[PDB]
Image (cartoon, rainbow, N blue to C red; front, side, top):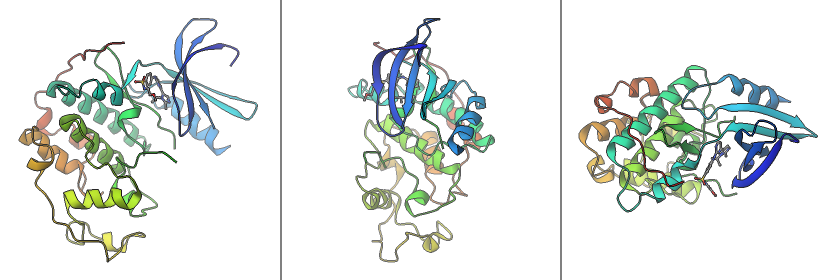
Length: 276
Ligand SMILES: COCCNS(=O)(=O)c1ccc(Nc2nccc(-c3cnc(C)n3C(C)C)n2)cc1
């Protein structure tokens, strides 16, 4: 750590505190994360998971029983960018570009059997070049808003499909400028999903009733059309979103397959208006 100079406290919570810092030698600006063995080997395997849409992990510093992660620095997260776009919302071309890039990023980690497990606007970082990247991979006050239903129902060995679900929720949020399922407890989260997509059963989700936390007493809500869930979204988008929000993790579209959906027929890479 003697090689770094803390510039300011970026973010906080969860895995630790994050600071913007400068390398006392090179002057290189980075994101320094102070984390609060197995972890070591797992984190190291991450330094190899390099992709343009994955915030690059520069170094892993383990000293005095303390773990420091040095990352490539990005100037803003999606949360802040959405809040700054609330008045007019993010332009479709830019929403589509971000989704396309994240799917590319996911298709890559998934191919390497790595899942993020906690995708959310706060850990999606953007630059002035129009790129968006996945941050805070890894392996209270944490948002459950983007949690996949299988996790909520107690699935112990959930798949990469959970990242697809989270991304679908983020997609809907960019389009409507409002969180899709803002649960404030695990059961509320589950019930918000149920009220919108319908209480899942053996028909739409084989085996769902045999899940750890599934209760036969769950209220039975009927599904709602996506025309009502994300109105402005054209048919291609609504079609893709519905496949990203499928209950059956085995039926949920994969990232790679998602990249082939017609919604991306006219995908481009616009530049956002960032006021750093
Ligand atoms: C409460 O205040 C929120 C402010 N959000 S922000 O001002 O738009 C903002 C968020 C993140 C960053 N920079 C950043 N770059 C690389 C990795 C990283 C990183 C590495 N590990 C983590 C957890 N992160 C971030 C997601 C914090 N954070 C710069 C500015």
